[PDB]
Image 1 (tube, rainbow, N blue to C red):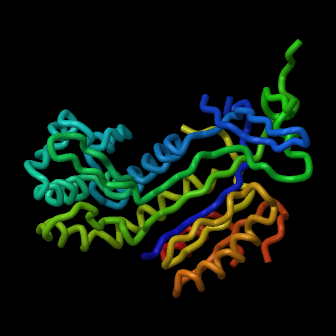
Image 2: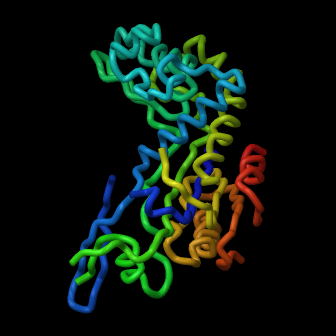
Image 3: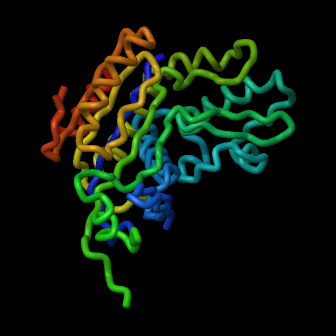
Length: 293
């Protein structure tokens, strides 16, 4: 299956950021030090992504559900939601596919972003868009000092932090070939013909929704660099911690392609950072257009 994956580096405004935290571990000469630093959750990123997809879908005439249209991504998770949406719950395990397809036909956000209905016969559709946590980018020759300069952490009277911005990174995976494809076991249902007809447009819209995550719910941030891959095998680029993450990504890309017997392995780069790369594009817009091809 074709997937689009990526690793991105953003310069984030600390005032705008400052509340989730996550651990960072430093190996010292006399042991390990664990400190918690501010992060942006994948859930927050997913909300921004899904809100953007709602706007695209409405512009493009794709179906969006009642609650999703209001940027309320309850997404068919309870009987109250189903009543609001006008969808009957699965009557048995064999009705799971009918239900999933009906939900997908009602709401492209539940298709691309997945959903989970808890009930008598539960149905879970995993998200085709997978967004990692956005955490501090651990680059350069003075990593622990930079963390101390940015955050109220000490790796060993209380004043304001020294600096005003920090580099952050996250990674993502979009399983584009699984968009509009049912995930539940069952015999074919009629609505699948209509999903097939809408698939190309749903995929394009999901790719377009990447623009607002990648261009910089979320704090003020500036795109520094990214590498985004297109593979016909599972692949995740290097996290954007080391400055050689783009170079290292291409190395592993080639190796994985051979190991997993792949036919497609394209890589696109945006570099507003001056880092070494070794297809370089100018803007996120140009990336979107290329990923749609």
